[PDB]
Amino acid sequence: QVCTGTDMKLRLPASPETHLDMLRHLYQGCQVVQGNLELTYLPTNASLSFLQDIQEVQGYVLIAHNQVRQVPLQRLRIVRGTQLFEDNYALAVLDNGDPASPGGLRELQLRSLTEILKGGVLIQRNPQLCYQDTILWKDIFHKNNQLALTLIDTNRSRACHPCSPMCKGSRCWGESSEDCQSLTRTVCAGGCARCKGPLPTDCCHEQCAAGCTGPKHSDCLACLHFNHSGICELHCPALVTYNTDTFESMPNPEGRYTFGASCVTACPYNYLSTDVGSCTLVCPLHNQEVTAEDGTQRCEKCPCARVCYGLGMEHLREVRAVTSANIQEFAGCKKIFGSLAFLPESFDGDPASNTAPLQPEQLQVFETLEEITGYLYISAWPDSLPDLSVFQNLQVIRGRILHNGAYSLTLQGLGISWLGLRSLRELGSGLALIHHNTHLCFVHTVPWDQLFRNPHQALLHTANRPEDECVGEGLACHQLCARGHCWGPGPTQCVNCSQFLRGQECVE
């Protein structure tokens, strides 16, 4: 039902051939996307039926470089704009069309889109796309949307039928009567932000987003603010309430944490239950996470300890890689509050600053690491290291921060023959992708279901050592391994032991 979004922008996928699986696993059956929704570089005949469910995007929606003729986000209603494309646009459709039939997105058919809270719209360089000029974008933009700006590229290369004859004002996202625009703001009596029609009787409860089916807080089709068990309120009920006479704090049985635009009993697995009554991925300043017995984590106020940070956080916020210059900052860590990334640059070095290449002996810094808050991205690696022994003691990747916003773990272009991640027990989020590691095997030897914690997790893989070639060398899990399942060759690599261990080897 709820899944996170992505942060790829216009970056090409590392493995385009796995792109549809990436998207299917991340979004199939997801109605609400935390963060941004991005579809970039899809093929003409791509199958995106799994995205028919999305109703809401917290951030921006980007459709770009897609030759996909149809992108059926027909249930999308609300784009919140909490983060914007180019820091300004809630919606962007870019580069759709070729330079017997041509590819390129033809129409958007967003029959459901009625609200943009923040951010503008960009529909540019899309020679095969029509009806981007047939929307009353100012109605969609919310009353409090200061960037109610739409830029349309009308230099089209395709002849199109005018909007369905059934569209009011000829306002549509397409040629069908089902592709016509609904109006929720600029048609509202009394100047109310949202309504379901032209009468004062049609004004929606203030707490409603994108319209309503009636004036009650239970009639909102979506909340502007928060959904408390179907009830829209301007805030979630205080997690801790106050005494009638003294106003002293006391637990609120009706108290909830704010999650997205919903109120929850407790924050979802791998989210932080902040003491203030909110759900985060990252604790507020001067609050540390505390792990709960139920798999949730909570943020409580500290006088804080020194904390290990990874990429995308703090002073490493603008740093996209682990290098020989910053590898030492992970010394002594059990957990990293951020991501790790090993790029060819990490291992090639960078003469611009006379920085030495990262050496394999420096990767030992992660041997004490049990948990990664963000993602682990390895697109380079010493070939002197046949496995990932470096992370053999890694137990958990929370993946709150994903690579390109999609992967909690990606490995590509390595000389490793097996992974060997003996201690890995959990993947909190995102997908994993392994590719173009033609020496690598022990891919199908670890049911990945044992590490996954939610319905949107999957392993994507390609261009690894062919399974047939690997087993042809006699490479298989030791018969002593529980279920014959392992991370690599040898009894030392068993996912579990049927008998007992000798050190890490399963023995009898």
Image (tube, rainbow, N blue to C red):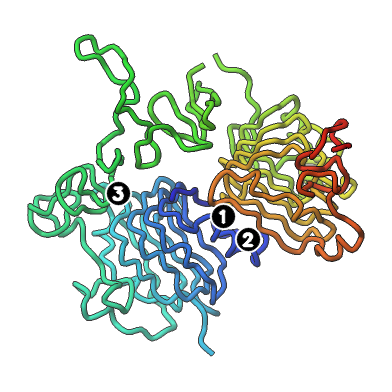
Query: In x, y percent, where is residue 320?
Result: 65, 44
Amino acid under disc 3: Gln
**Disc 3 crowd, CA 10 A, few/some/many (<14, 14-19, 20+):** few
Q: Quadrant of residue 9?
A: bottom right
Tell me which label, 3 or 1, sits earlier in the chain: 1
Residue 385 shown left or right of residue 241 in the figure: right
Q: Tell me which amino acid carries mark 1.
A: Met
Q: Is residue 46 visible?
A: yes
The answer to the question of whether label 2 and label 1 lie on touching residues, with beta carbons closer than 8 A, is: yes
Picture disc at residue 146: 3
The span from disc 2 to disc 3 (Cα, nearest Å) is 33 Å
For the residue carrying disc 2, how many other residues have a C-alpha within 10 Å: few (<14), some (14-19), or many (20+)? some
Q: Position of residue 183 (x, y in %)?
A: 21, 62
Please give the residue where the numbered disc 2 appears in the rendered image.
Answer: 13
Residue occupied by mark 1: 8
Q: Quadrant of the C terminus?
A: top right
| Residue 245 screen position, x and y as percent | 19, 10
Mark 3 residue element: loop
Residue in the picture at 45% in, 69% down: 71
Residue 237 appears at what percent x and percent y? 29, 29
Q: Nearer the viewer, mark 3 or mark 1?
A: 1
Vertical comparison of 332 with 430: above or below: above
Nearer to us of marks 2 and 3 is 2
Few, some or many C-alpha atoms within 10 Å of disc 1 (few <14, some 14-19, many ≥20)?
some
Cα distance in 3D space between marks 3 and 1: 26 Å
Upstream in sequence: badge 2 or badge 1:
1
Viewer-proximal residue among 205 and 480: 480
Residue at left 34%, top 25%?
Answer: 239
Q: Is residue 87 above or below residue 469?
A: above
Residue type, mark 2 in image: Pro
